[PDB]
Amino acid sequence: TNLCPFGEVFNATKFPSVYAWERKKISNCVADYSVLYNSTFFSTFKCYGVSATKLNDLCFSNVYADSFVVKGDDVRQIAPGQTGVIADYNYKLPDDFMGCVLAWNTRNIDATSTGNYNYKYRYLRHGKLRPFERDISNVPFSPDGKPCTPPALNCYWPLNDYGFYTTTGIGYQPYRVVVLSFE
Amino acid sequence: TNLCPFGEVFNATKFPSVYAWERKKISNCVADYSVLYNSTFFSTFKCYGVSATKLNDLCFSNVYADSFVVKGDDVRQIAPGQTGVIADYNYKLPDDFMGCVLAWNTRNIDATSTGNYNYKYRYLRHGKLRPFERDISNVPFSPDGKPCTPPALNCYWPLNDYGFYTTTGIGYQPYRVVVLSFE
Image 1 (cartoon, chains in turn brown, yellow):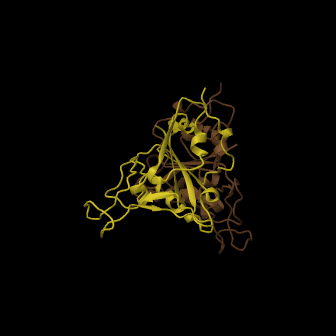
Image 2 (cartoon, chains in turn blue, red):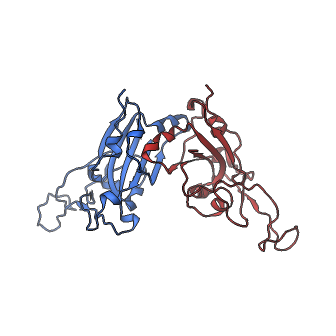
Image 3 (tube, chains in turn green, orange):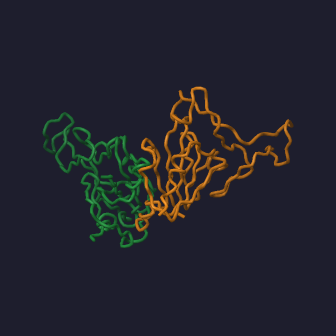
């Protein structure tokens, strides 16, 4: 009884911004993938920290699922040991990560001809994130560390919008991402 | 009844050369990964053609398993859409591949300080292989296509040995590869 709430993960109408990534717990449930929508085709499906003795982990029966959107060229940062703005300041996996990263192109729902700017990422921060840390503040940033009031000079806004347009290359298109941690 | 022949696949003492890659069918059985070896940790675990409604394919219940050895720098050729000597002349995945590619570093058992030369690959051929095609011939090769009898000019032997040494970078180290097709 109780089927896994994978629909809430893969088929959610809205996905979070990566700076505001969301986690859902999946445990103590039966998996029925037949009640998900068809046509969710993973262009990335990469698993880390898996051993032959623990191949049963790919049944996904006890899992945390983290969801967010990035641009295509940033999907490579959702891996252990990566650097760049997403890994450093938004969503960080541990080096010893045990889990899988799934991504799929969502140009058709997440991009517009006029530009969808609803998804954001943090580009400035005082410190990189530890693994599975999350920062949701939107506080003026000063390089020197001092508190800071716009329009003061050397005072910056730490988030930047992705701009998702319908007529750009794949590296600039939106990807929904789900990271499953074996647990 | 019947526990999966995964031991035969993952735990074999000798692996095939990639030109002479081997296939094993795994179906009508229940998995017991416990008897497999601890210490087999996959440095590559990448799945292709998966969709959300087919996530259960990752239980690996009905599956062909292809095994062989390549060097580290060649593992990237074991993916859909790749070119190079291995993809072209040894082992070809189709563009529409539905399955997972697993690899792990085996310097410890497949490389020697003196050089292990038991693993081979084809480096000369007239034409690229079709997906899942296997060529185990070893007849002399002429670039003009004509029949060939060594020791004549423009006559060559089409297979080369990998040389696996203990004291080399990871790109030159041996990797055991298991490709699991959801077929």
